[PDB]
Length: 138
Length: 135
Ligand SMILES: CC(C)(COP(=O)(O)OP(=O)(O)OC[C@H]1O[C@@H](n2cnc3c(N)ncnc32)[C@H](O)[C@@H]1OP(=O)(O)O)[C@@H](O)C(=O)NCCC(=O)NCCSC(=O)/C=C/c1ccc(O)cc1
Ligand SMILES: CC(C)(COP(=O)(O)OP(=O)(O)OC[C@H]1O[C@@H](n2cnc3c(N)ncnc32)[C@H](O)[C@@H]1OP(=O)(O)O)[C@@H](O)C(=O)NCCC(=O)NCCSC(=O)/C=C/c1ccc(O)cc1
Image (cartoon, rainbow over all chains, first blue to last red; front, side, top):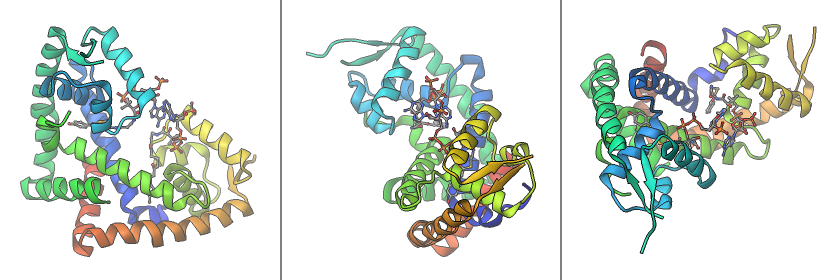
């Protein structure tokens, strides 16, 4: 299937392929603490925004209800966060906080730094901006 | 949640959010012919590379084998392609592909390009291709 036709001129294709490659690298770099990007993002949102419910987290990360529930089942079964009553709030446990701190360090040092070096600082920044604009306005 | 911490400065996160929004718009625009992005891309590669096999289509698209087998069962069951002793587009496949390509270019990709600069769009395309190729 060597000829790409219009695929190699379509932004969505290139976006998807880049997204896939970055995920695969994330997974390898963060493997010592066994997080997917979404797992990492959730823990990271929980630690930065305590006392939020399961809906605020899922909606902020564009994850659908039954998908979010399944992912909470995994995180909670691993002892990384807890579901706990609202006067359905979510809290990191100590184990959560510890795996998160380690993950942040692997992500920055091992994964993000290499992507920035590949791209260069100006490109990286213009890329991040254009991506943010697609997400926000497209 | 509202504080985004490091998420808002991480490349992969922005990449994923951008990808999601683009896929969602694609689905909306190509909806008269009922194709996901990967379905379109499989039909397109088959059309452009007649006589190549399952495994080469899948590996060029970065699709694993059992996922690929499942997507061919759907495409074959819709009468869009046939497994024959290799993969072949049917006439109905070629007709839906042609229609799709138009909807993609006119309603979807054109709008994306207009949002960004024409120049910013070309540079985005090229940076994404670099990530896919080299990272
Ligand atoms: C490509 C696959 C084989 C099919 O994707 P799809 O055509 O969008 O099909 P679906 O989204 O309907 O279903 C995929 C699976 O996710 C499942 N799924 C559904 N929602 C749920 C749920 N809420 N909970 C859990 N499971 C669920 C779904 O049921 C299904 O599993 P299964 O039913 O067991 O076969 C996909 O599953 C996959 O393996 N992706 C990983 C690799 C990959 O994406 N490679 C790139 C392919 S090429 C490409 O994306 C092109 C993009 C493009 C973009 C823009 C353009 O202009 C041009 C091109
Ligand atoms: C976020 C979910 C809920 C969980 O993803 P995951 O943590 O990677 O976990 P899994 O890969 O183990 O997927 C769990 C289930 O989804 C299935 N799935 C799902 N897409 C498929 C498929 N294309 N084919 C085949 N099976 C599938 C998958 O097989 C499985 O189903 P099941 O076996 O029945 O429990 C995901 O499934 C989902 O619902 N939607 C994708 C929407 C979404 O990505 N929103 C953004 C979340 S935030 C984010 O991604 C951040 C990235 C980031 C990047 C870099 C950074 O530095 C920082 C952050």
